[PDB]
Image (tube, coloured by chain):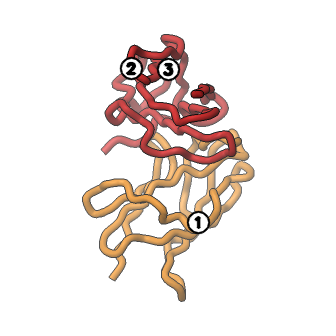
Chain colours: A red, B orange
Amino acid sequence: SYTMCSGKFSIDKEMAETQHGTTVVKVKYEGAGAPCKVPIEIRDVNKEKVVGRIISSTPLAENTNSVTNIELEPPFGDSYIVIGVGNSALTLHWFRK
Amino acid sequence: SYTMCSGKFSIDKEMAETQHGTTVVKVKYEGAGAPCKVPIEIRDVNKEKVVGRIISSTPLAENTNSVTNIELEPPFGDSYIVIGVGNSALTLHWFRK
């Protein structure tokens, strides 16, 4: 249906907590082959994948220069959010008490 | 850790059944940014993501042109293995009697 985006993402709005438990971040897609899927991995303190943690519906870069809203529910402890692929990828961090 | 590849993959040796209950494939990475983790998704007949079926510990492409070996446990029935990102990602069908 869609494959995962090859290209670069930049941060459009800095990650912030919502009124509910949640975290939101906005990214802008700079690459090609859109529409395509935003690659998102959430990892724990060890290097491990955490599933089921993504609130936003199946998240997509519609176009080059489109903007995607990603809402997550980070797990307890330290977590890292990896957006995109390659050297270009953005690696984010969150702490939940 | 390493990020997922961004580059193109080709098929070094097509997927084949094992003596045990698995298949194996070799893919060659023609992209840059290695070392990088081979992006692998296993999907079902409904094209839905199926989890827990990658046998090999997280497959890597060490270098450009490096060849790789992936051992997977395909679901019974029709399944689809998507390797890589973007327009250039390989899509593979397997059928398990």
Q: Residues within 10 Å of mark 3 (few under 14, many from 20)?
A: some
What residue would you read off at disc 3? Answer: A30
Circle 1: residue type: Ile
Circle 2: residue type: His
Farthest left residue in view: B46
Cα separation, mark 1 vs mark 2, equals 41 Å
Q: Position of residue A96 (x, y in %)?
A: 57, 28
Q: Position of residue B63 (x, y in %)?
A: 74, 50
Along the line of sight, the residue nearer the viewer: A2 or B22: B22
Along the line of sight, the residue nearer the viewer: B47 or A47: A47
What residue would you read off at disc 1? Answer: B70
Q: Chain of mark 2?
A: A
Check the image and report above or below for B69 versus A45: below
**Quarter holding residue A57:** top left
Judged by depth in the image, the label closer to the viewer, 1 or 2, is 2
Element type at mark 3: loop
Q: Chain of mark 3?
A: A
Residue at x 53%, y 39% (from the top left corner): A41
